[PDB]
Amino acid sequence: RFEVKKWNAVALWAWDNCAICRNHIMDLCIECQEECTVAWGVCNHAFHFHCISRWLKTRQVCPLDNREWEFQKYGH
Amino acid sequence: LSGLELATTFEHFYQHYMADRLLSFGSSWLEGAVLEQIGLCFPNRLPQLMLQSLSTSEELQRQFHLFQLQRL
Amino acid sequence: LYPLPYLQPTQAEWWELLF
Image (cartoon, rainbow over all chains, first blue to last red; front, side):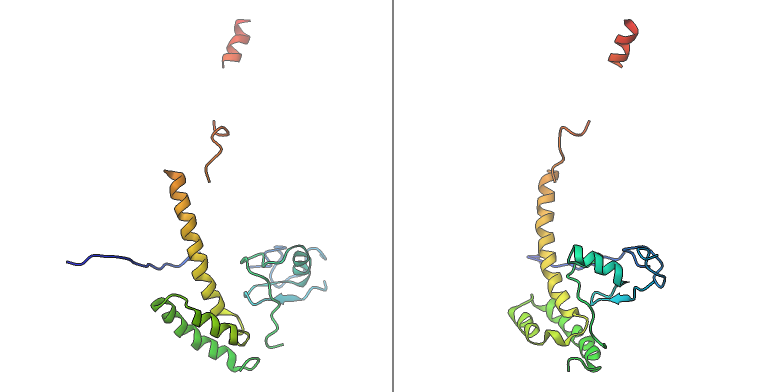
């Protein structure tokens, strides 16, 4: 016979417009509703530069995934 | 390699070995040190996120213990 | 988180009727 002394198990947390201002993803910015370009970040979300400018000026985390927002500068 | 096109494919390949290495051994000093050297090469910062994931999981273990106590 | 024990949960109507 065998006996278990320890163990480790694994599982995944299985579960798209500009959520922060809720306008359509490709549409314009409600605050100004037309000069906001879209912004991308390392955490792979797309938000309005207006939305993000304000929000970041308030708080310094990604509002969608709880990580320090980093303006994506690859490929640029 | 940083800032070039090859970064994405290198990172894709690196993830695939860092996975098995973390499941075979806990996140040692070695992985964190190598990353503190070559981190800015990885464009999306996936490996750092795997490492941080292990730590978040230990925190969750603490909270689960407390929750059991409250139920009892 | 232990819940607030006091927060969690007619005679006056009757008395009104009697009166």
